[PDB]
Amino acid sequence: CYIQNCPLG
Image 1 (tube, rainbow, N blue to C red):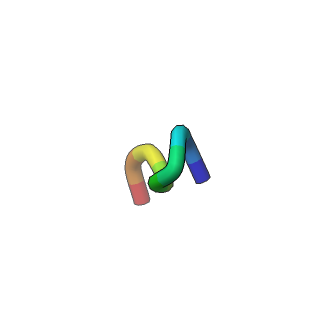
Image 2 (image 1 turned 90 degrees about the vertical axis):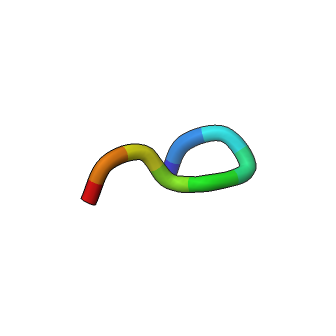
């Protein structure tokens, strides 16, 4: 994922 959320994909 990324921050609280996921990056690409």
